[PDB]
C-alpha cells in the first residue's frame, strides 16, 4: 500500500538515523515501565485513554501489562538487530517499523481509539507477535544488509516486497 | 514479509 514512501525515500543521514534509534529506546523504556511499574501503568491509562473509567472495567490493567511485556521484548530485538547490522534502518522508509509500537505509545493515537478498538488490538498483538519472530535476522539477511550500497537496490529490494 | 504483514 505504502509505495508512496517507496517512491521518494532517500538515505537516512547520521542524525536522522539516531533520531529513529532514540525513539525506539524511549518507547522500549516506556513499555518496560508499564509492566514493571504499577503506578506507572495506571497513571498512563488515566491520562491517555479518553475514558479511563470503562477501560479498567472492560479491559483491565492485566491485559495492558501483557502487551507491554511483549512490546518491551520486541523493542529489544529490533534494537539488537540495529546494533548487529548497521545498514538496517537504511532509508526513511524504514521509519515504518515504528508503526508497530506507536498505537501503544502515542497519547493522541490511544486517546482517539475506543474501548473495543483497544481490546482487539491488544488481542491481535498478543497473537501475532509471539509467533512472528520479527527483527530476528538470518545470515542471509545480515549478508544482504552488509552489502547494501545504494537506495536504488534497496528500493527495488523492497519494491519487490 | 513479517514486517509488512503488520504495517
Image: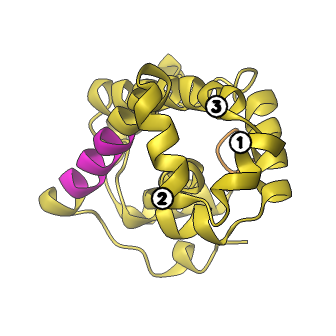
Chain colours: A yellow, B orange
Tell me whether the residue at label 2 lies in contact with that at label 1, contact meaning CB atoms closer than 8 angstroms.
Answer: no
Residue A142 is left or right of residue A70, and the answer is: left
Query: Circle 3 is placed at which residue position?
Result: A67
Mark toward the start of the polypeptide (3 vs 2) = 2
| Residue A16, above or below A138 | below
Taking the spot 48% from the left edge, 51% from the top edge, the residue there is A105
Q: Residues within 10 Å of mark 2 (few under 14, many from 20)?
A: few
Say the numbered circle drawn on residue A47. 2
Say the numbered circle drawn on residue A56. 1
- Callout in the foreground (3, 2): 2
**Dot 3: what SS?**
helix
* Front-most of residues A150 and A106: A106
* Front-most of residues A123 and A97: A123
Label 2, label 1: how far apart the Cα atoms are: 13 Å
Residue A151: % across, % down: 38, 63
Say the numbered circle drawn on residue A122. none
Does the magenta-highlighted stretch encompass residue A138?
no
Mark toward the start of the polypeptide (3 vs 1) = 1
Residue A116: % across, % down: 86, 56
Taking the spot 50% from the left edge, 24% from the top edge, the residue there is A35
Do callouts 3 and 2 point to residues on the same chain? Answer: yes
Residue B4 is left or right of residue A22, and the answer is: right
Residue A1: % across, % down: 73, 72
Task: State the residue lying farthest toward the front.
Answer: A53
Mark toward the start of the polypeptide (2 vs 1) = 2
* Front-most of residues A104 and A88: A104
Residue A159 is left or right of residue A145, and the answer is: right
| Residue A132, above or below A150 | above
What span is colored magenta in the figure? A17-27
Taking the spot 63% from the left edge, 67% from the top edge, the residue there is A50
**Dot 2: what SS?**
helix
Quarter holding the C terminus of chain A is bottom right
Amino acid at each position: 500500500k505504502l509505495i508512496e514512501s517507496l517512491q521518494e525515500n532517500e538515505l537516512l543521514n547520521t542524525d536522522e538515523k539516531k533520531k529513529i534509534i532514540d525513539q525506539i529506546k524511549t518507547m522500549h523504556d516506556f513499555f518496560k515501565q508499564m509492566h514493571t511499574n504499577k503506578g506507572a501503568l495506571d497513571k498512563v491509562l488515566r491520562n491517555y485513554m479518553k475514558d479511563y473509567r470503562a477501560v479498567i472495567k472492560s479491559i483491565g490493567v492485566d491485559k495492558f501489562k501483557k502487551v507491554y511485556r511483549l512490546l518491551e521484548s520486541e523493542t529489544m530485538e529490533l534494537l539488537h538487530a540495529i546494533a548487529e547490522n548497521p545498514n538496517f534502518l537504511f532509508s526513511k522508509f524504514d521509519r515504518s517499523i515504528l508503526g508497530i509500537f506507536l498505537p501503544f505509545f502515542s497519547k493522541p493515537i490511544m486517546f482517539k481509539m475506543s474501548i473495543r478498538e483497544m481490546d482487539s488490538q491488544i488481542e491481535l498483538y498478543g497473537t501475532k507477535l509471539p509467533l512472528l519472530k520479527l527483527f530476528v535476522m538470518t545470515d542471509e539477511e545480515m549478508n544482504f544488509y552488509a552489502n547494501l550500497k545504494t537506495i536504488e537496490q534497496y528500493n527495488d529490494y523492497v519494491r519487490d516486497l | 514479509x513479517x514486517x509488512x504483514x503488520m504495517x
